[PDB]
Image (cartoon, rainbow over all chains, first blue to last red; front, side, top):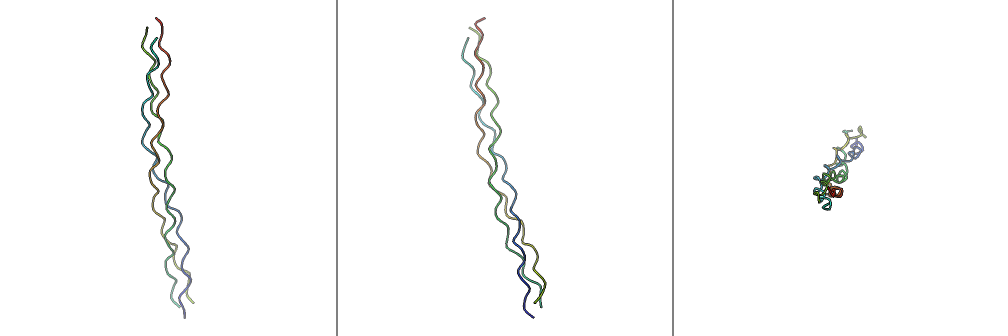
Length: 31
Length: 31
Length: 32
């Protein structure tokens, strides 16, 4: 008796973490 | 016959989405 | 031949995303 078929490929891994927060927006122009 | 071999590992997950926006800048100083 | 093999493991976690975009510019200051 030969070996059974190899099992299905695993499912895709988790999505990566989101990046770190962007830099603060600049101050508006002076009045 | 013997059971088949374990399947291959799944694909790597997709790289993460962009980080959240930076905080909005403050209004400009008074004149 | 024998039974089908077990499912393979989940893949590895993806790489972290890029840095966020900079915040919105502030509104114009008041004349006062």
